[PDB]
Length: 257
Ligand SMILES: Cc1cc(C)cc(NC(=O)NCCS(=O)(=O)Nc2ccc(S(N)(=O)=O)cc2)c1
Ligand SMILES: [Zn+2]
Image 1 (cartoon, helix red, strand yellow):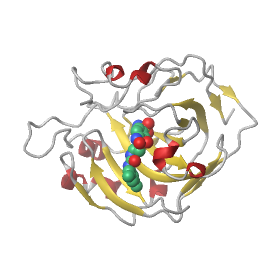
Image 2 (image 1 turned 60 degrees about the vertical axis):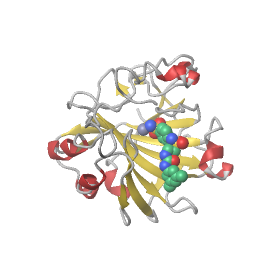
Image 3 (image 1 turned 90 degrees about the vertical axis):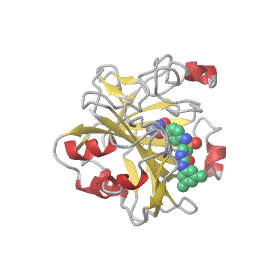
Image 4 (image 1 turned 180 degrees about the vertical axis):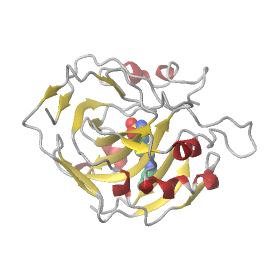
């Protein structure tokens, strides 16, 4: 089964998921001098006021906070998107050191981590149908750099002790994902894929220009999680990021000048 080690990491994924070598794989490097400002792009609409978080979980690949997506409660709209996309979950990718961990890069710069808020297009009815469509998902990507603490992240960080190993989950209601956003919603956008198996090419990526800052104590808490399940040799959950993939016949558009 897949992971991020020498023998099961991103260089192996194509054997079970041959779309790993596809025409619209993610993440990619964002060359800021080649992305074109697109004035036709609208502002993004992030409507998270009615978000209903449910649980926090260690899935062996990362940790995730899940939301009730049975109604339009927390939706992403506008920007490059047609229609309404409901927030399903968010999770992160992070490094063993502050100089690596993000999946997207910006002029080859790697950030310490990257947040993915995962949304699906309601015209397809359920997430499973949406993953089979080229416009099925929209993932909002936010870079993390190490500096000042992010107060809106601290409730996440303080429960990680309780889901140390894969398969563990905990109640995590009443969490406000608005506390994870930077000030600016300036973004880059391009068509891409899931960055973990099945690597489906179903994602409109929206990557925010402005990173959020998190403290060294907060990211250290990410790094104490485990890939393994309880009672198995401890392998720290670090460097759970896929590297940049070929851009091929794609063009990255910027919402700003
Ligand atoms: C059944 C149920 C219910 C609720 C509420 C949440 C969940 N959690 C969930 O579905 N997680 C993944 C959905 S996926 O699209 O199939 N996988 C995927 C997503 C994003 C990326 S990424 N790294 O490109 O952002 C990579 C892979 C499940
Ligand atoms: Zn992700």
